Length: 186
Length: 193
View 1 (tube, rainbow over the protein chains, first blue to last red):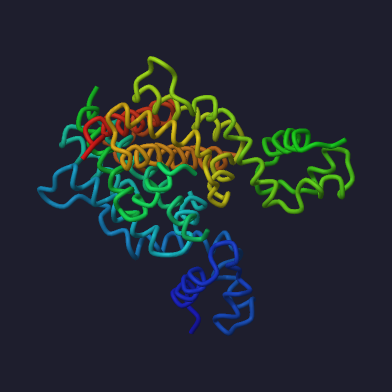
View 2: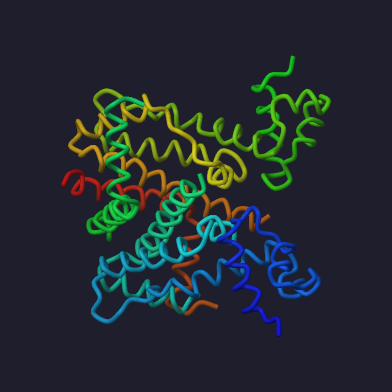
């Protein structure tokens, strides 16, 4: 009647309404029209709830973990990064929740693929981690702005807003991938 | 008698001892050997204290914020990135504190100097700002992961076993420098449209 799936769906709706800081087990119980005891063995504390929301966001939206057949390493890393970013952007404070929470089958497939595409084994692992670091940093800043000078600067900042958030993100990602080209091996 | 400099000096020592989660204004007042009103004048809540800690922790980065004469854009961006990483690593939960702080307006003078320098070095104004922001994004992501691993301390196949063993032991600096060098190498080609 009240299963894990039902609780998480209500928690994600509530997260979007009030955000990470305001989200409590009390408010979730009230949203579900149940007493607080009825949530305890699902999620014993806010930490347990946030862990489950982080997991749910990635399971739902992060689809490009594995390379597709005949896929180029540049396309794979970009699609993986775009997929991860979409997952973190899909709910309010997504990046903050992910960072506050921190599969050998998946890892081996990814590393084997990059090694075949010319990456040194260590540099394959470093490249995957570096893309993840950039995505978390970027989404944290974007979502922080959502919640919240000279003539030269004023005109430039206006022109940057016009270009949009995707343009800024893609420039950093394209630069990281372009840089891997020459540093793939010592 | 009690000034903000003396208060935050004590707050930094306490942060290293107990961490961000255990830090309270009451524990700070006790450490300073002052009464609650004396501290309350400086900070009425933990949020205000965290804001002040976050601003102080960027001291190391401010020393590498301005381009030096006879230094190219590549050395400037790398040394700036390394100083930002050192600043966030200098205290327990540094990256979490930086991330948790509501977005702060930058020094407009420092920003313009940085942007105008990159423009002189063959960046277009837009891509100069995108490059500076991209470096900051990478550093924050990297230090969050590194500090989460430290906080947590307090079977793979034959293909991955020894590889994964080597990576861990040899340290965090090689991985960070690889991502940073890749980002800067990438800027070289994408500097202008």
